[PDB]
Length: 496
Ligand SMILES: CO[C@H]1CCCC[C@@H](c2ccccc2)OC(=O)[C@@H](C)[C@@]2(O)O[C@H]([C@@H](C)[C@H](O)[C@H]2OC)[C@@H](C)/C=C/[C@H]1OC
Image (cartoon, rainbow, N blue to C red; front, side, top):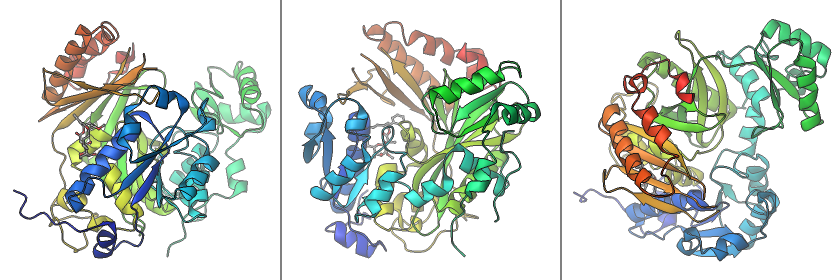
């Protein structure tokens, strides 16, 4: 029944009839592949629901010579495209100044970067803002305040959120508005400038521990120390790899689970949690199997993790979608790990159990629309689809519940994407991107067992094909293990 569907004539009427302040009808996508297809597809569906016009919000995509040559699907999907230099991403998708120049010349009113590339570079929203261009993500001020790993951990401690023992343990900031910030003098105290103090901090932290360079990433500038004897060599190896960068130390995550809490915030300080996900099964800094919601931790503890994630977001003035990752231990304790100031490729797991269109939520949020005025958010909280009545996310009268269970798996064998459909289960969707390479499969079920079963069946179907006639066999064995099937806490060995 569609009789109660409310629609407007255009983006302008939507913004005015929904308490927004900025009209966005043209968006520049600084990304390709599945990210670009996903972004356009999600928002277009929303445009159909709100304007009965799938193309009400036009899209412009950045295209490299390579992508255009392989006639990537995302290109044809866009209303317009702008050819850009090829080569590494620093010459295109991750080039902050290039993205901005394009956004202004078209011009568009907003930019979406997705994940990867420049999506976590605070200078992007910073430069966009200075040019009157909205960003479908957190503001630079929100990333400057949350800062890196050092800053955010310090911030977490200030809000009294448990953290792992590190060279910054105990540091806190002094804490109406005005987001929290970390003084440079406080920050430096969390870094180690030399082997000598590095050895003193490592003694109290205890081994094994990680020596990390904040400016480092993607397996770069990281090193694991097992003893005070190897510390010096390792510490200096990090200096050599990423010279001139601040360095901190952190206790190594023993046998813990990794839980993430999905966050969504508006431009008025409101924020809500969209349950969370479990990404414990990893293979050397790589999410292999993910579940939603998370169920390994008791609901009351997990709700506490949600409360901490929201306080952390509000205090720094976060805006848009984001993820707070926690470490859950065998006992029952948890510690803040980090906060991903952007959407991740696995956000659909959350979209499915919360029936929330994340990309469309991002777009409306950047238009100035308050959380309580988002249809999906109102329904999640059991309110009227089009009501204007504010919602108490703290103590709601209609406890929001997650619908079903989701299992996502990374599969392995540019901008070209291949949609995978299975004759087995109509409740599974997938894709993969040729260089071949990787992709992801997503499975839904009324409960965890049916979600796992649907996944196993679709994966068995993939094995039949040539490309994945072996590489997906380890996932099927993993998914059908007793320990996984029984949803046990001790499954760190599934990593092998
Ligand atoms: C690249 O586009 C793919 C992406 C599929 C992603 C996985 C899939 C899924 C999740 C879990 C298990 C199985 C399948 O998620 C979904 O279908 C749901 C959650 C969702 O993403 O659908 C999209 C939006 C309405 C919205 O963003 C969200 O709805 C709330 C629509 C536009 C479908 C897009 C697809 O196009 C065919």
